[PDB]
Amino acid sequence: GVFNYETETTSVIPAARLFKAFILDGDNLFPKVAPQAISSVENIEGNGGPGTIKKISFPEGLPFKYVKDRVDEVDHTNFKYNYSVIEGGPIGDTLEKISNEIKIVATPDGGSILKISNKYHTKGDHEVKAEQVKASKEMGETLLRAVESYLLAHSDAYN
Picture 1 (cartoon, rainbow, N blue to C red):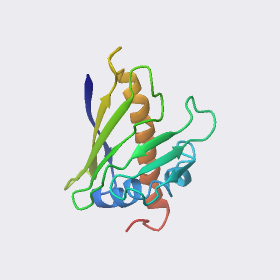
Picture 2: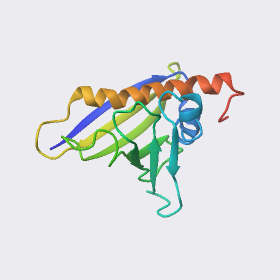
Picture 3: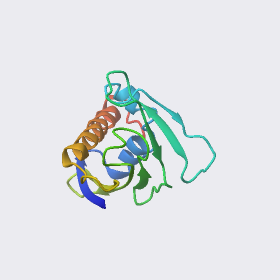
């Protein structure tokens, strides 16, 4: 009973840059440029290389505790990022596993669009709640905005 939440977002930053900074360096940004969304990531070790895990931890006031993500390999030339949320967040209820695939696209006059693919893997019970898909899509849009204005404020970081 998986759900295919194929959504997307828009950013003024070109695809490549948005990737090297908002998708390749979110651990040294999300918290800095977005201390309101992330607090610090812990793991990124070298145990599985392509497909390792990470422990993202938000600041207090969170209804959850943290979130482990699976890089599931990563791209670069075509700006692609196949990762997962697995354990972490509102786990339980009706959402145990979650595989997300992202694909940035550069436009001749539209900056870059982030094609997000939230594949939810719940376990029977009720179906994924769009509202829930929105909360996560909310932290994702806010972060994109953080790394979006971080490149301009700083000296063109990730250039």
